[PDB]
Image (cartoon, helix red, strand yellow):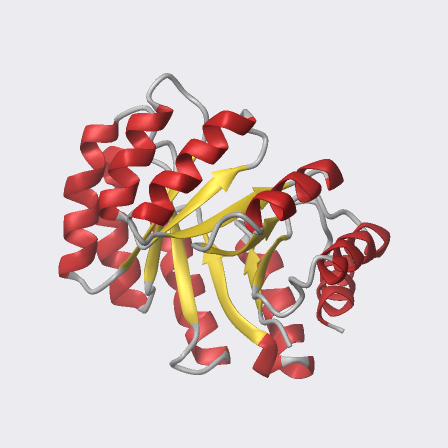
Length: 233
């Protein structure tokens, strides 16, 4: 079956969810995407590594390009294994240095590709630097096809960020055209009913077994667990 990644920026909420997942479905938990203050993220990373095994992957979100390397070094020292660079479309020339320092640490590089004047240049740079690219499905279709074709040719894993059910249909169709496609980042799930609709669409597309990420932004602890279990059944 598929494995679950969880994205949550609140430490108290993430740990409460993580403790429950460890008790119920520890072997299905693949990793966590964490963010926030360096002091909070580093404490979360240690807590998550204490809960789960040394095999737990932890992605630290970097939202400030000029502070990314310092936050990355401290997070990796806590046990993080990957970075997710957001806001790269503003200053594309800054990603090489960040990606170079990530590589020197043996850290995976994930680049979030969102809209902007330099979105194609960001996509090109991400293709030359990143292990994986997260493509916002809300992007215009021709732009998304461009980014996916660029990443595929570079051998970069492609992750589709989806929020609407129509975004799911878009990403599913494009996923079948993208060999580099690796999985979905599920945003907007607010109850088990929405989690069921996604699970059914993924089943109809034959994409169930791929690991996915569930963003917990729109969920409380009990609904996050119920939505996670609903997607994983």
